[PDB]
Image (tube, rainbow over all chains, first blue to last red; front, side, top):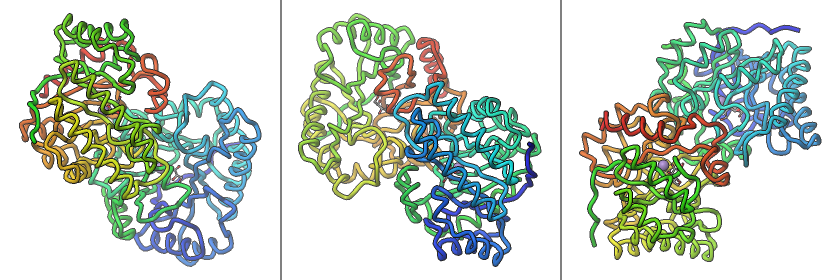
Length: 287
Length: 287
Ligand SMILES: O=C(CO)[C@H](O)[C@H](O)[C@H](O)CO
Ligand SMILES: O=C(CO)[C@H](O)[C@H](O)[C@H](O)CO
Ligand SMILES: [Mn+2]
Ligand SMILES: [Mn+2]
């Protein structure tokens, strides 16, 4: 068991272009990501059964584009649950997601894979956390057979009760104790929870395996409150060489299964291409 | 008719010291605010029927302290509801809170007074917004007879679907069209939703009636990401002369119902006096 190769590469989140993964939606997102000049598309596998693999393989080939995958779990698939029937549903979704990612020749399963994405009605018990750590052990081991790293995305208090800072994320990963399990940081969530935009990156070092770039309000990069200068300087200091996906959500493009959960009440952009294009330039200028 | 006098004065949120307003909790919080050097205490009126008003007035006299009030409504008192019985409950609580604030000699009712504080399942309908605007018209007119201004606190996407930016708040206040209705900004909520920390303040000018100071993670002022230098520069430029309350919420002090609502999963402070004391020094040094 070991970590699978990572490279400095730039990706666009599928929801920048498409709210579904129909033949049309898949192509819109892949074509968009390719058009803006990204190395990969990040597919939202919130329902990995809805994904036509052959179709997707063909599109990625057609546009000379690589794929990674992210998801959140839901109440019905929450691996922190003290109901083992719900944890089993979680393990199953995570296996299927991995199977799909393997069929597409992808190497990264990231996002909120360790709990239900959304507002918890109270703080996590030690048992909620232990349930989550075990589930990520079973996932990392399943993934390892298929040349896939998992990257646990730290998100803000409103989207998980398990880990809200990189430091918390790192301590969680110590317990997972798997070589193909990494920290996933997102500048949007960091903007809320972190003591500056450097502390968690510098602590993480080689354990930082994935990055999401989002503005404070998840709109155009450079129109919000995120100190990107301080963040990217930290990446340079640890010489980060892994996926970097631009992520943004507008009511304009809505997945029913994500948009209400992320409380995307506001339209912060309408031109996917203009947003994605400016974002990659903004990112590449700094890293 | 008219708006009531505002002065530049510094406030401590009662919830920094006490989770309740028992005689002991009230005494503790008022003595705390006075000890830290604040001009007033901001009393949480989530349940204004549970306040002993004569006791509170005696305490405020005893410690030579003024009082303003903030609250959030809940599902059962949501003035945005399409259930007129629920709106009626909201009107009733808002009237009661105004009565309490009036008897206490206060002039400012602020916070999430226009909707239920928390995660909405979907975006706000035209009805939801119109119901809210009408409720704030009835409240503003009721408060006008009692020399009280109302200030509508703009909160982040996870805490309301009605208004997430200062600009949205100003537009909502245009429809309310009451001289004693003002905008209320909170740096914690601005840190997520705003295009920088100056814009909403410069646009609001004389319509900014109330300010909450919160760090990005709601911990010690200056250990987070909020560009306070840029915010206070904006306050200076419009010569803001209104209440400035420091707030933060510890799961060790507040009611489990509120800490769960605000997703306080960790505590970045334990010493109420040290936090509140240092918070005021931080504020008074910049404004
Ligand atoms: O930031 C996120 C949600 O706020 C993550 O990117 C999600 O886990 C991922 O996009 C799943 O949609
Ligand atoms: O920022 C706030 C909520 O997060 C407001 O201060 C509260 O809604 C209000 O003070 C009630 O406690
Ligand atoms: Mn993300
Ligand atoms: Mn506030």
